[PDB]
Every structure is written in C-alpha cells, then in structure tokens.
Amino acid sequence: HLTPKVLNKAQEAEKLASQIQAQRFSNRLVAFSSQYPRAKLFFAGIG
Amino acid sequence: CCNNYFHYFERYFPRLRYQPFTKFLAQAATVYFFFKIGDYYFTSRRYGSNDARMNGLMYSNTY
Amino acid sequence: SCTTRRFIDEKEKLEYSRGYNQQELEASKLRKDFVKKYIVDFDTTLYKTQVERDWAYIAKREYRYEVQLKSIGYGGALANAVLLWRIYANKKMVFWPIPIVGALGYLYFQPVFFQKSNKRFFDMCNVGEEYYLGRERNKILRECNKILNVEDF
Amino acid sequence: ALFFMANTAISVPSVLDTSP
Amino acid sequence: PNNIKGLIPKTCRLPATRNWYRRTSSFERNGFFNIHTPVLNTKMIPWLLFIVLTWGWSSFQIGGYNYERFDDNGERRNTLYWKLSPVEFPQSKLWNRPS
Amino acid sequence: LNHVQNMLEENLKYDAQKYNDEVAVIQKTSRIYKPTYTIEFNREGEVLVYSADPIKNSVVYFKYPYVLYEAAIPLFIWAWIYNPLELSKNAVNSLLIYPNIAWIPRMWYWRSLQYKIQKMYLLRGGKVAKIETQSLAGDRFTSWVETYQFHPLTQDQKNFDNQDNAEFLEDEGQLKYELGVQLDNLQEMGTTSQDIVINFMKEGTVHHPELFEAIVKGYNIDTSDYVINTANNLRAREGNHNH
Amino acid sequence: ILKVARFRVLKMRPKISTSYRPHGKWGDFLACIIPLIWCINILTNSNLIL
Amino acid sequence: YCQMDPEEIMRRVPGITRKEAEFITKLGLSPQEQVDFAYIAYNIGLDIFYFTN
Amino acid sequence: NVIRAQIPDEDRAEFEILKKYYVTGQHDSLVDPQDVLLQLDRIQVLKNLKMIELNEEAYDPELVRLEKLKARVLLEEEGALLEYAHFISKRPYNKPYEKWGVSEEHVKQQILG
Amino acid sequence: MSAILKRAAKYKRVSSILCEGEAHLRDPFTPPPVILKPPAPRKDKKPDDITDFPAQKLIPLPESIPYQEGKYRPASIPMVAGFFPYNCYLQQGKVYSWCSCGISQSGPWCDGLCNSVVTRCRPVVFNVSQSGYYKICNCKFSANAPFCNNTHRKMVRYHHQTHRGFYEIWGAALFVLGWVYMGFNYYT
Amino acid sequence: IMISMPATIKVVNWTLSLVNGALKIDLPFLFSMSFLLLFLVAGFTGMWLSHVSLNVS
Amino acid sequence: ENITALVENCKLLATKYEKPQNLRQAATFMKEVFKLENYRKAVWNRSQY
Amino acid sequence: MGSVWFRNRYWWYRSLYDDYVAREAKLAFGIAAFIWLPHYYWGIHLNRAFEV
Ligand SMILES: CCCCCCCCCCCCCCCCCC(=O)OC[C@H](COP(=O)([O-])OCC(O)COP(=O)([O-])OC[C@@H](COC(=O)CCCCCCCCCCCCCCCCC)OC(=O)CCCCCCCCCCCCCCCCC)OC(=O)CCCCCCCCCCCCCCCCC
Ligand SMILES: CCCCCCCCCCCCCCCCCC(=O)OC[C@H](COP(=O)([O-])OCC(O)COP(=O)([O-])OC[C@@H](COC(=O)CCCCCCCCCCCCCCCCC)OC(=O)CCCCCCCCCCCCCCCCC)OC(=O)CCCCCCCCCCCCCCCCC
Ligand SMILES: CCCCCCCCCCCCCCCCCC(=O)OC[C@H](COP(=O)([O-])OCC(O)COP(=O)([O-])OC[C@@H](COC(=O)CCCCCCCCCCCCCCCCC)OC(=O)CCCCCCCCCCCCCCCCC)OC(=O)CCCCCCCCCCCCCCCCC
Ligand SMILES: CCCCCCCCCCCCCCCCCC(=O)OC[C@H](COP(=O)([O-])OCC(O)COP(=O)([O-])OC[C@@H](COC(=O)CCCCCCCCCCCCCCCCC)OC(=O)CCCCCCCCCCCCCCCCC)OC(=O)CCCCCCCCCCCCCCCCC
Ligand code: HEA
Ligand SMILES: CCCCCCCCCCCCCCCCCC(=O)OC[C@H](COP(=O)([O-])OCC[N+](C)(C)C)OC(=O)CCCCCCCCCCCCCCCCC
Ligand SMILES: CCCCCCCCCCCCCCCCCC(=O)OC[C@H](COP(=O)([O-])OCC[N+](C)(C)C)OC(=O)CCCCCCCCCCCCCCCCC
Ligand SMILES: COC1=C(OC)C(=O)C(C/C=C(\C)CC/C=C(\C)CC/C=C(\C)CC/C=C(/C)CC/C=C(/C)CC/C=C(\C)CC/C=C(\C)CCC=C(C)C)=C(C)C1=O
Ligand code: FES
Ligand code: FES
C-alpha cells in the first residue's frame, strides 16, 4: 500500500523524471519549428 | 627516473590526478611501449643490406 | 604498364557498378578467401622459392595499396565528416569519432574494394604449377572455371 | 652518394619468363 | 526616408568590432599615408608562403601525378609484350626549378 | 573641372577650410579627475594599474571554429588524391586551393590574442598610459597612448559605452567583465593605426581601480599628490608566465 | 626573407647595429658542408657513369 | 606626441635643466627614449638645441 | 599520523576513513563494508565533478553545468532529479558557442556559432 | 568624475608585486625600498632651475661580487652560454672569476666582455679550499653560482613549456624523424 | 668543382648582411636583390656543367 | 554604372542607418536600397550615361 | 641540433659569423619536416619506374 507520500520521494521523482527526459525530442522539434516556420514547407517540397 | 612526469601531466590531464587507477594504467602502458620497442628492435625483420661493413651491428636484424 | 593498370581499374569499376550474379559472387568469394588465406594473412617470406616469395610479395603490396590504403582513406574521409559534424554540434573539438568511425568506415569499405579487385589479386598469384602457391592458385582457378562455365587464365 | 637516391625498390623482382 | 522597418537608425558612431573587413593601409596623425602596416605584415604571410615554398615543392609532383592519371605518363600504345617493351618514365625534370 | 558648380562640392570645400582654420592642435578640455589618495609611483615614474596573462588564460590550440577549418583539410586532400568524383584535371586540382587558405583564420586569431594587454602603467601627469603586450612568439610590444584617445565599449562589444556612467568595475574594484576599449589612434612599432580595439580580461588583477576607470573613460588624472618608491625589482626582458 | 620584409624596415623595428668588426673564424668551414656534399654527389655520379 | 613630465625627467637626471627637459619632451621620442636621451645629454654636455646638418 | 600529515588535504578524509576501517571495522562483523564503499564513492563523485570542471571550464559551460547537476543527482539532493530532467529536456542537440573571444572576429563567424 | 569619486569609497587597491618578487630580499647589493616625499611645488618655476627632489643613494657597479652561498640572483638577465655545466678541475686556493653575464669568450671564467656588454651582472670572484672537479654553471641562472645546481634542466623544461620553444624543439624533432623514417622506408 | 665553395661563402655572407639591421629600401637595394637571385642560378648551372658526364652532352 | 549606382545608394542608406550586422540584415538592407526612390532615378540616369 | 651542443653559444655565433639567425634557423625545422613528403613519394615512384 505504502500510504505515506514523503517517504517515497525518490519513487515520485523518478515517476516523472523519465517522462521529462523523454520529452527532449519533442521539445527540440517544437523549438526548431518555431525558429524556422518555413522549414516544414521547405522539407516537404524537397521530399 | 621520470615518475614525476605523471604528476606533471596532471596539468593537462586531471584524470591522472583524480583517478590513481588511470595513472597506474598509464605507467603500465609506458612499460608495455618500451617492451614493444625492444621486441621490435630484436625480433622485427628490419631488412638490411648484406654488407660486411655493417653486418652484425644490429642496424638491421639480418642474422 | 600504366595503361594496363588504368584499364584494369576502369574495368573493375565498371564491373562493380554493373553488379554481380550468383555465380560471379561465388567465384569472387572463392578468390577473396584464397587471397586472404595465402597472401594477406600469411607472411609471404615463409614460402620456399625466391620467385614465388617475390611474386607473392608483389601481389601482397598491390593488394595493400588497392584495398587497405584505399579503405583507410575512405574511412578517414567518413570519420572526418562525422568529426566535423560533431565539432559543429558541440562547438568544440572531439576525439572519440576518429578511432571508432575510422574503424567502422574501414570495415565497411574493405569488403567492397576487395570484391572490386578480387580477380586481379587472384590472377597475380599465377606463379606456375611448379610451386605450391601456383598449384593452389591453379586449383582455385579450376574450381572457379567449373562454377562459371568459362575458362580464365 | 650514401643515400642520395633516398630509396631503392628492391620489391621489383626480375621478370619471370612465361614461355611454353 | 526617416522611418524604415528593418533598418535601425544610426544615432551614434559604431565601434570597429562591427566592421566586416579589416583595413590594411592607415594614416599617421600628420597626414602621411602608411601602406606598410602590421596588418599588411600579417596578410603577406600566406601569399609569400605560397609563392616561395608550398607551390614550388608540390607543383611538379601534382603535375606528374595528374599526367600519369589522365595521359598514362605519355605512353605510346600499340606495343607488344610490355615485359619486353621499354618503360615510359613518369615526369622527372622539374619544370618549376630553373633548369 | 572647377568651372562645374556643385553645391555639395562647395559645402565640402567650405567645411574642410573651416575645420582647418578653426580646430587647432591645442584643444581645451575639462575632464580632469583628482584621485582621493596619494599615488605611489615606481622608481621609473609610473604606476601600475592592470596586470594579466592573456596567453596563459586563453585557448590557443583547440579553438572553435578553427579546429573545424583545419580538420576539413584532410577531406580535400583525400578527394584530390583519389578523385572520387571523376573530375577533370583542372577540376580536381581546384580541390587543393582549400588547404592553402584554411589556416588563415587561426593565424588572425593568434594575432588578435596579442592585443590583450598584459600590463598597463600610468605616467607622471596623468596624461599618458603605457600598455605592454606579448605575442605567442615571445615578442613584447610596449606602446604609449594619450588618455583622451580611449573609448570603452558595452559588455556586448557592439556599441560604445557611455564614458561618464560606465559600469565595468565591481564594487570592490575588480572588472565585472572583460572590458573592451577602442583607441582612436595607436602607435605600434612606430606605425599609427586607426580604431584599434584592445581587451582587458576579467581574469586579471586590477590595481588602483580609480586610476584604471579614469584611464578607460579618458579623464586626465591629477598626480600632484604623488610619492616615489625606489624598488628595482624588475629587470630588463624579465620573464613571466604570459608565454 | 619573411622576417626581413616584415620587421627589419625602419618603420617597424630597426635594430641598433653596434658591432664594429666581424669575428667569424670557422663559419666558412661550417657552411661549406653543403657545397662539399654537392661536389661529392657530382663526383660520385660522374665517376659511376665514366 | 606623448610628452613625459619635464619634472619627472629632471628627477631621473638630477643635474639636467628644465628648459632642456622640456625641449626633449617636445622632441618626438617615446618617454623611455626621452629619459635616456636626457641622461646622455646631461652626462656628455651635448647641446640638444642644435639642428643637425 | 605521519601519513596523515604528508597526505593531501583533499583526500585526507578518504585516508581517515580507510584508517578507521582498517583499525576497527575489519575485525567487526556488524560493520558493513558497503557503507564505506558508498562514502568513498561520494568522495569520488566530488573528485570527478572537480576533474570535469577543470577539463571543460574553457570549452563547455553547458557541459560543466550538466555535470554539476549530475553530481547533485548522485548526491541525492532535493529536486536534483527533477532539475536534471528539466535540463535534459531543454538541452539543445547543437549547443550554442559561448566562448567567443572578445578580440576574435565574430561578424563573419557568427553563422557557425 | 562624480561616478568615479562615488565608487572610490568602495574601490580597493592591490599590491603591485608580481612573480619577479622583491630584489632586495635576494640581492645583497639592492637596498631596501624607501619612499621619498616630493617637496612643496615651486611657486615660481625659473627656466634654468634644478630639481629639488630629495636625492637617492647611488650604488656604482662593482668590479666583481663574492660567492653567494646558494642565494645568488643575477642583477640582470644573463646570456645562456650553455644548457649543461662544465666539469672543470679547480686548484686549491686559486681565485677564479666565474662569468655571470654569459657572453665570456674564455669559457666559464670572466673574459672582460661584461664591461663591453650592457648588463649589471658582474663576475663572481671565488676561491675553493679543496682542489678537484666541479660542475660550473653555464646557463648563469644557478642559485648556487658559480656551481651548477641542475637549474639548467628547469630552464630546458621552461623552454619546452613555452609555446614557441615547444614548436622549435618539436620541429627539430620531426626534422630528425624525417631522416629516421627515410631510413626505415629506404627499402620498398 | 672545388671553386664552388667560395661562391657559397659569398652567398651566405650576402644573406647574413640583410639580417638584424635598419633597412632603407631603395632601387640600388632592389637591383642588388635581383643580382643575387640571378647569380644563385648562374653559379648553380655552372656547377652542374662541372659534372663531367653531363658536360659531355 | 549599375554597380556604381548600387554602391553609392548603399553608402547613402548606411550613412543614416546602421550597416548590416548579419546575412538577414544585409538582405533587408539590399531590398530597401533596391526599393529606394533615389536608387531608381540614379539607375535610369546612369544607364543613359 | 647546432648551438645547443656548445656550452658557449655566444662563442658559437661569434666564431661562425658574429650574426644571429638562430630564430629563423630553428623555426625552419617545422616547415622542413613536411615540405619534402610529396617530392620523396614521387621520387620513390620514379625510382620504381627506373627499376622496372
Ligand atoms: C566575364 C565574367 C563576369 C563575372 C561577373 C561579374 C559581375 C560584376 C561584379 C561586380 C563586383 C563589384 C564589387 C564592388 C565592391 C565595392 C566595395 C567598396 O566600395 O568598399 C569600399 C571599401 C571602403 O569602405 P569604407 O566606407 O571606407 O569602410 C569603412 C568600414 O568601417 C569598413 O567596412 P565594413 O567592415 O563595415 O564592411 C562593410 C561591408 C558591408 O557589410 C557586409 O559585409 C554585409 C554583407 C554580408 C555578406 C557578404 C557577401 C556574402 C556573399 C555574396 C558576395 C557576392 C560578391 C560578388 C562580387 C565578387 C567580386 C568582387 O561592405 C564592404 O565593405 C564590402 C563587402 C562586399 C562583399 C565582399 C566579400 C565577397 C565574397 C565573395 C565570395 C564568393 C562569391 C561567389 C559568387 C558566385 C559567382 C562568382 O574599400 C574597398 O573597396 C575595399 C575592398 C577590398 C576587397 C578585397 C579584399 C581582399 C584583399 C586581398 C586580395 C584578394 C584578391 C587577389 C587578386 C585576385 C584577382 C587577380
Ligand atoms: C545566404 C546563404 C544561404 C545558405 C543556405 C541556407 C542555410 C541554412 C539557413 C541559414 C542561412 C544563413 C543565415 C544563418 C543565421 C545563423 C544561423 C546559426 O548560427 O544557427 C545555427 C543553426 C542552428 O541555430 P538556430 O537557428 O539558432 O537554431 C537552434 C537549434 O534549433 C538548436 O538545435 P536543436 O537542438 O534544436 O536541434 C533541432 C534538430 C531538429 O531535428 C531533430 O530533432 C531530429 C534529430 C535526429 C537525430 C538522430 C537521433 C535522434 C534520436 C536521439 C536520441 C538520443 C541519443 C543521443 C543523440 C545524440 C545526438 C545525435 O535539428 C536538426 O538536427 C535538424 C537536422 C535535420 C536534417 C534532415 C534529416 C533527414 C534527412 C537526411 C537526408 C540525408 C542528409 C545527408 C547529409 C550529408 C552531409 C555530408 O544550425 C543548424 O540549424 C544546425 C543543423 C544541424 C547541423 C548541420 C548538419 C546536419 C546533418 C548532419 C549529417 C551527418 C551525416 C549523416 C549520414 C547519414 C547516412 C545514412
Ligand atoms: C624507436 C624509438 C622509439 C621511442 C619511443 C619513445 C621513447 C620515449 C623516451 C622518453 C625519454 C627520452 C629522453 C630524451 C632526453 C632529451 C633531453 C636531454 O637529454 O637534454 C637535457 C640536457 C640536460 O643534460 P644533463 O642530463 O643535465 O647532463 C649534463 C651533463 O653535463 C652531461 O654529462 P655527464 O655527467 O652525463 O657525463 C657524460 C660522460 C662524458 O664523457 C664523454 O665525453 C662521453 C663519451 C664517453 C666515452 C663513452 C664510450 C662509448 C661511445 C661514446 C660515443 C659518443 C662519445 C662522443 C664524445 C665527443 C667528445 C668531443 O661522462 C664521462 O665522463 C664518461 C662516462 C662514460 C661511462 C660509460 C657508460 C656506459 C657507456 C655509455 C657512455 C655514454 C656517455 C655519454 C655520451 C653523451 C653524448 C656524447 O639539456 C641540455 O643541456 C641539452 C644539451 C643538448 C642535447 C642534445 C641531444 C638531445 C638528445 C639527448 C637524449 C638522447 C636519447 C636517445 C634515445 C634513442 C632511442 C632510439
Ligand atoms: C635568396 C632568394 C632565393 C633563395 C633560393 C633557395 C635557397 C638557396 C640558398 C643557397 C645557399 C645555401 C647556404 C647554406 C648555409 C646558410 C647558413 C646560414 O645562413 O645560417 C647560419 C646558421 C647559423 O647557426 P644557427 O642556425 O643560428 O644556430 C642555431 C641552431 O642552428 C638552431 O638549433 P638549436 O638546437 O640551437 O635550437 C633548437 C633547440 C631548442 O631547444 C633547446 O635548445 C632546448 C634544450 C633541448 C631539449 C628540449 C626538450 C626538453 C624536454 C623536457 C621534458 C618535457 C616533459 C616530458 C614530455 C615527454 C615525456 C612524457 O632544439 C634542440 O636543441 C632540441 C631539438 C631535439 C630534436 C631532435 C630529436 C629527434 C628525435 C625525436 C624523436 C621523437 C619521436 C619518437 C618517435 C619514435 C618512433 C618513431 O647555420 C650555421 O651555423 C651554418 C650551417 C651550415 C651547414 C651545416 C649545418 C649543420 C650545423 C648546425 C646547424 C644546423 C641547423 C641550421 C642549418 C641552416 C638552415 C636551417
Ligand atoms: C661572368 C662569367 C662567368 C662566371 C662567373 C662563371 C663561373 C663558373 N663557371 Fe663558367 N663559363 C662562362 C662564364 C662564367 N662562368 C662562359 C662565357 C663560358 C663559355 C665560353 C665559350 O665557350 O664561349 C663558360 C663555360 C663553363 C664550362 C664549360 C661548359 C662546356 O663547355 O660544356 C664549365 C664547366 O664546368 C663552367 C663552370 C663554372 C663554375 C664551376 C663557375 C663558378 O665560378 C660558379 C660558382 C658558384 C656556384 C656554384 C653557386 C652556388 C649556388 C648557390 C649558393 C645557390 C644554390 C641554390 C639552389 C640550388 C636553389 N663554365
Ligand atoms: C620574395 C619573392 C620570392 C619569389 C620566389 C620565386 C617564385 C617563383 C614561382 C612563382 C609561382 C607563382 C604561382 C604560380 C601558380 C601556378 C598554378 C598552376 O597553374 O598550377 C601548377 C600546377 C600544375 O598542375 P598540372 O596538373 O597542370 O601539371 C602541369 C601540366 N601537366 C599535367 C602536363 C604536367 O597545378 C597545381 O599546382 C594545382 C593546384 C594549384 C592551386 C593554386 C592555384 C593558384 C592560381 C594562381 C593564383 C590565384 C589567382 C589570383 C592571383 C592574384 C595575385 C595577386
Ligand atoms: C644531418 C645529420 C647530422 C649530421 C651531423 C654531422 C656532425 C657529426 C659530428 C661532428 C663532430 C666534429 C665537429 C668538428 C667541428 C666543431 C669543433 C668544435 O668546436 O669543438 C669544440 C667544442 C667546444 O665548444 P665549447 O663552446 O664547449 O668551447 C669552445 C669555446 N671556447 C673556445 C671559449 C673554449 O666541442 C663541441 O661542442 C663539439 C660539438 C660536436 C658536434 C658538432 C657541432 C656542430 C653543430 C652540429 C651538431 C650535430 C650533432 C651530431 C651528433 C652526432 C651524429 C652522428
Ligand atoms: C620552391 O620555390 C621556388 C622555386 O620553385 C617554384 C623556384 O624555382 C625558385 C627560383 C626562382 C628564381 C631564381 C627567380 C626566377 C624569376 C622570377 C620569379 C621572375 C620571372 C618573372 C616573369 C617571368 C614575368 C615576366 C616579366 C615581365 C616584365 C612581364 C611584363 C608584363 C607586361 C604586361 C608589361 C608589358 C609592357 C611593355 C612591353 C612596355 C610598354 C610600355 C611602355 C613602352 C612605356 C609606356 C609609357 C607611357 C607614358 C604610356 C625559387 C627562388 C623558389 O623559392
Ligand atoms: S662576467 Fe661574463 S664577461 Fe665578465
Ligand atoms: S648549468 Fe646553470 S644550473 Fe646546471
């Protein structure tokens, strides 16, 4: 059960740390798209 | 003679300073390098001319 | 012989661009195995006759220049490209890609150059049936001729 | 002189006769 | 026009760090035009190097290598039994060096 | 040619003549700074205000993007050697142009490294500053510049910082950031150059912060309250860590 | 050549030549090694052809 | 044009004159060279106010 | 005592730990050597942080900051894992160059930066 | 100057002593530093007036200096005659004038070129109570001058540490490696 | 062939005369440089002619 | 003459506005110079010249 | 590699020429260490051609 919450601080942190680290790729894509809004169209045309 | 050079090189390679295992590996690598140099000198083909003027001087491992 | 060397190199390039079929690939595999066993991975100086030793060493040096050095150059070019990419990415100098990427490029490029120039190395070992190396070369040539349903020198 | 040529191609062997 | 969107008004003297190009010559405060300056001294290094050492020590070898690549070192074809035929030597006379 | 009349040309001629007739060598100024404390000058009549070892504290060999520039050379050399693109003779020879030009930017960077002032002194009268610098080859250049020719730049180096209200010294006296200053006219090796930019690295001790700030801002320092200390602790061509 | 063209001009870095007279005694001998090697090579090749 | 202090020049060479120090400062030499020239002139008795011909 | 006097102060603490262990915990069953190993590993974490700071002080401010975050995570400081995860998420693949020289040309080379 | 005056309150001065240290603690002939207070400014500055600044003691150049027992610091920077010492046989009780400037044409001993070169380094006149072989310094930086104390090794190390000295040493190294590689690849 | 050595001595002396001095570039100086450049090749070709086997051709 | 007119118009624009700092600033500066009213008249007159 | 072998380097310079070109002489080694590689390799190729 593990009713206490503070006593599982490491587990609670690691619960979201993996997701936050995994979100690196998406954040970089969003930043690149914001920096170069025309990049999407340019790459689509080239492809 | 030159064990102090390992400590001196910590200026550019702090890994030796902060990891004595690295310094031991470096010393072993130096010993192995000298070993390989000697083995190359005395065992490698090191082809040379068959000239009486210099045969047997170890300039070439002809014999 | 510079004309002959250029013609042979161009023929090899044209064949590589063309590609190979099952029989050609099998013959090339046999020739490459023979060359690696008897020349590349063997000390040529250990043969019996001076003529066979000298010709085997000539073949080994030709293989070196046409395969090993070329693969080293191409792998170094690839490793340098990767090094430039990583240097731009990290805004600093990196040393890891040089050895690893160079070794990977050499491993990738050695098989293709060996396939391209397998026939030349095999043919350069035709010292003659009077010697062990020439006899093994003739045996492999007979096997390849049987496989390919053709005759070669 | 001693090493004026700076290199010798000892690898190049005497051409082997290939007559029948 | 006094209002341009992209441009930024020039209300002050810009520093030398904004210059795309570095001047070679200069002026003394008494009006003398200096052509020889430390900028020229540092600029003349690569040109003199090319003129003196690298071109003179690599040109002939490059030429010979290209000649062998593209012209078979001037070999005359239509010959028989290269083993008996004479060898057409690669370029050996340094044309860059005064003969 | 003079018979052709142009108002712009006439204005230029009038401006030149008026400038020549009006502005003289002697120029009046009122930017005089009186330091609170008495100045202790060396035996040579100079007071040290800045010291640093820019060569020691700077990166010389592995500096981006010069490492990239020089690491691109082997690719060109290999391309020329092996002709992977099946080019003509002239086309392949064109690949050898890069190695002859790929090391110039590193040379320029090394040259710029010598403009980082190693030491600065203020002379008697508070009107002349001697800047001593050294190059990577050990050559030492000392140049004297009048104080009014200094102009500090902002922390971004893209503009001139206000001389009056310039914030480049910490509260205690040290430099907040590497301070760039442009000298209008610098006489180096007996040659005068225009708009010479120099830098004082933050990794350098600053002596007499008031005097340093006055020199940077271009004030004339009043050295009436001065004392002379006889200390022959410095020898000619003295060695240092700035190598 | 580079040093003379870059620094030895009066404008950049003239040097006060205080030396009165030369004092070389064997610099000629030291320098003549190179022409000596030239002569040795010439003699060797010529004699081998002869 | 960076003229050194004539009083400083006089202090470094005690026996030199103010007029001589000022003339040396007016002469276009770097301050170190000005001090050295003042020292040499005082030690030799050379007349700095002489136009060489 | 003499070894302690001659030993550098940076690893004097490690020497003290080793001496105390060799004297007392070698002969004691209840003393777990894993705890001593963990203490030595914490000291080694500090040493590695200092080493990496020295190595990358003049090259990668971002890398040294990331390694400081990693050292905090290893030491298990409050919020260390969360801040490390945020830094990783916000970390660019092509990190900007932050060591431009003041005297170095920047107008033409800013594209690479 | 308002901002400068305001910040002067919290501005702090730092000592102007650097790696060269103080010469009076290492040179017997260098007097301890003394501060001289200028007199009051002259109300009238006559064209032909002389300095009223207090006089400074004048120490002439000695002809020679005694042997410093391991505490020798050359007055000027001497020429590096050599990077390794001279193994010279000294006689008992014979006075030797070791060269300090480093340009002497008579070897380790003074030849007189110190008087002809601009330098404050004076010859060291010394005597030995026991005849025999001694290593006399040649780099002229030994703290135990005239006797070598292996300071030439540290001078060589500093030369190698310098950017240009490193380049020169390793350029010569690779030049010799050129011969070595030519010999190694002579047969091909 | 032995005659070549004094020419080398003169060449090295000329080269050393240009170092560590106050240069005053002038047309006579440029003519001197051109003279040196021509003389080097001239003497080198003479030394080559001294080669007996090459001298035959 | 087209090159001369372009260079002179660029100088005229730069005397009142800061010179380009990067490629984008240079591109917009060139576009503004091209669309300048004075530039077109100068180009026409110098083409006649 | 020259003056280093001599324990009187000033004497070395004076007795050779009384001139100082040591800076250029010792800087030239770095350039001379590689200015010869293409020539050496082409000479090896030419020697092999002569042998053939
Ligand atoms: C039949 C064949 C036909 C072929 C086609 C021909 C077509 C026609 C071509 C016509 C070309 C016209 C060119 C006009 C130039 C006008 C310059 C001018 O007026 O400047 C005044 C200037 C003084 O102005 P100032 O107001 O006193 O300056 C004060 C400022 O504080 C100091 O200034 P600043 O630091 O503030 O800088 C301001 C900056 C403005 O700020 C900027 O820089 C902003 C713009 C950034 C982008 C830069 C260019 C990007 C790439 C495109 C460039 C296209 C160039 C096309 C023309 C090339 C040929 C010239 O503007 C400039 O100063 C000039 C910059 C111009 C660009 C220079 C770089 C060119 C690179 C070319 C790369 C290769 C391109 C290949 C293309 C494909 C086809 C070949 O003095 C000069 O003119 C000096 C020029 C020096 C040039 C040479 C430098 C190197 C010297 C070493 C020798 C190298 C050559 C050896 C001999 C080789 C031949 C034997
Ligand atoms: C007037 C001149 C005009 C010239 C033309 C135009 C030039 C461009 C425009 C600029 C014009 C002039 C004006 C310049 C203004 C100033 C610009 C400036 O300073 O900013 C710099 C500017 C970025 O600064 P910024 O504009 O401030 O933006 C900040 C960035 O967003 C910060 O970066 P970030 O962290 O946000 O990164 C975002 C990321 C967005 O992308 C991603 O997030 C995806 C990344 C996937 C990586 C793979 C692994 C993914 C999973 C990793 C998981 C973790 C494990 C560890 C991973 C470690 C890292 C790998 O960006 C990328 O990586 C984009 C690359 C996409 C390329 C296409 C890939 C698919 C097709 C490939 C076809 C084949 C190409 C062969 C090329 C061969 C070349 C020899 O530079 C760049 O954009 C850098 C681009 C990437 C480096 C260049 C080389 C990339 C390709 C390398 C290929 C290597 C060989 C591959 C062989 C494959 C064989 C099968
Ligand atoms: C394939 C390679 C792979 C390599 C991989 C990488 C390897 C990494 C290795 C890392 C470590 C490398 C270390 C390199 C050091 C470089 C720096 C250095 O040494 O300079 C510091 C050096 C400091 O010197 P020091 O250690 O303080 O010693 C100063 C003492 O005054 C010196 O005086 P002393 O107290 O030493 O006295 C010497 C001698 C003085 O007596 C003599 O006159 C010598 C000859 C005695 C007769 C011996 C007969 C046998 C045949 C001798 C043939 C040569 C004699 C020529 C005599 C000419 C006389 C005009 O003493 C005597 O009175 C006679 C004693 C005889 C006892 C017999 C012992 C058994 C036979 C061996 C005898 C060797 C004698 C020394 C020879 C020295 C060269 C001439 O700084 C300098 O001042 C530099 C000076 C210029 C140096 C130029 C040469 C540079 C290279 C030296 C190292 C050679 C290494 C070669 C290795 C080759 C391997 C393939
Ligand atoms: C006009 C326009 C047209 C022109 C057309 C073209 C031209 C035509 C011209 C025709 C006429 C030609 C005329 C020819 C004559 C010209 C003469 C003239 O004008 O010059 C007068 C010029 C005057 O002399 P100088 O050059 O001023 O004298 C200074 C020296 O030459 C400079 O040498 P230095 O030694 O005194 O200074 C450098 C010194 C600076 O260094 C020092 O002194 C420092 C102390 C030494 C030790 C330093 C290192 C200490 C390290 C400590 C430990 C560090 C930490 C540990 C790190 C490692 C371990 C972890 O370096 C050393 O001593 C140490 C170097 C050691 C490197 C060698 C070791 C090789 C092995 C290394 C192996 C390593 C890898 C292992 C791999 C194994 C497996 C493969 O030359 C002459 O005296 C006349 C020469 C006449 C010919 C004879 C040449 C031989 C005699 C000696 C001189 C040779 C060099 C100079 C030759 C001249 C050209 C460069
Ligand atoms: C000014 C006139 C002049 C000078 C100075 C010389 C100088 C020399 N001459 Fe010559 N010679 C002639 C004018 C001159 N000569 C003429 C007119 C004829 C033909 C006459 C007729 O038949 O009508 C002739 C013919 C002639 C022959 C006969 C060729 C033949 O008939 O086949 C030979 C043979 O050795 C010779 C040798 C030399 C030598 C060794 C020198 C030496 O003095 C040269 C020594 C100098 C050097 C050797 C320079 C060293 C070089 C350097 C330091 C630079 C090195 C740099 C590089 C290699 C890059 N000369
Ligand atoms: C103090 C002064 C000292 C002076 C010393 C005396 C110097 C004498 C030599 C001077 C040489 C000057 C340079 C010549 C360059 C010749 C290049 C050439 O054609 O290639 C030769 C060689 C010949 O190659 P090849 O393959 O054609 O061979 C010759 C022909 N076959 C094949 C038949 C043998 O080619 C190369 O080197 C290829 C790479 C060249 C890369 C550099 C090109 C430079 C182009 C000229 C400079 C740039 C233009 C603008 C210059 C502006 C100047 C202000
Ligand atoms: C290119 C490859 C290398 C070739 C090397 C060729 C040289 C081979 C060795 C020659 C030895 C004989 C030289 C005679 C001329 C000098 C005589 C002399 O002055 O001696 C007294 C000097 C004494 O010098 P000193 O400075 O101590 O004392 C003289 C000063 N007074 C007069 C005030 C006392 O002894 C030496 O230092 C001998 C040095 C011998 C080495 C050659 C020196 C010239 C520079 C080239 C160095 C090359 C090193 C090669 C090493 C060996 C390689 C196999
Ligand atoms: C390793 O590197 C090296 C080498 O290897 C490459 C070497 O070979 C060498 C050896 C080299 C040498 C010893 C030097 C060799 C010679 C050199 C470098 C110089 C050669 C120069 C040339 C060939 C250029 C040709 C010379 C010229 C004068 C060309 C002139 C051209 C032009 C267009 C001018 C034409 C004009 C006219 C004819 C006159 C018309 C005008 C008038 C009559 C007057 C008009 C007047 C009015 C008023 C209108 C060295 C040193 C080296 O370092
Ligand atoms: S001390 Fe060196 S010459 Fe008198
Ligand atoms: S030679 Fe000066 S200390 Fe050894």
Image: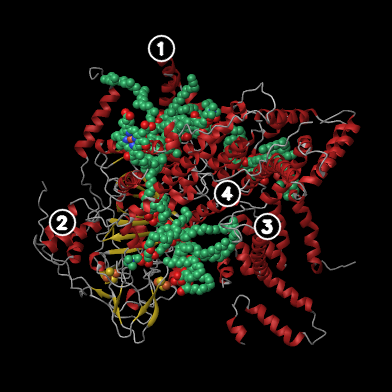
- Per the image, label 2 sits on a secondary structure element best described as helix
* Disc 2 with disc 1 on a shared chain: no
Q: Kindly indicate the quadrant of the structure image that contains residue E37.
A: top left
- Per the image, label 1 sits on a secondary structure element best described as helix
Residue F58 is situated, as x and y percent measured from the top left of the image, at: 49, 56
- Per the image, label 4 sits on a secondary structure element best described as loop
Residue F183 seen in the figure: yes
* Disc 3 with disc 1 on a shared chain: no
Q: CA distance from mark 3 to mark 2?
A: 79 Å
Residue J19 is situated, as x and y percent measured from the top left of the image, at: 40, 69
- Per the image, label 3 sits on a secondary structure element best described as loop
Whether the residue under disc 1 has CB within 8 Å of ligand 1? no
Numbered mark located on residue L48 in the image: 1
Q: Which residue is mark 4?
A: I97
User: What residue is rendered at 28% in x and 35% in y?
Assistant: K31
Residue C74 is situated, as x and y percent measured from the top left of the image, at: 68, 40
Q: Which residue is mark 2?
A: H22
Q: Does the CB distance between marks 3 and 1 fall below 8 Å?
A: no
- Judge left or right: residue F74 versus residue C147: left
The residue nearer to you, when weighing J151 against I90, is J151
Q: Nearer the viewer, mark 1 or mark 4?
A: 4
Report the chain holding disc 3. B
Residue C126 is situated, as x and y percent measured from the top left of the image, at: 79, 37
Q: CA distance from mark 2 to mark 1?
A: 64 Å
- Judge left or right: residue H21 versus residue C70: left
Q: Amino acid at mark 2?
A: Glu
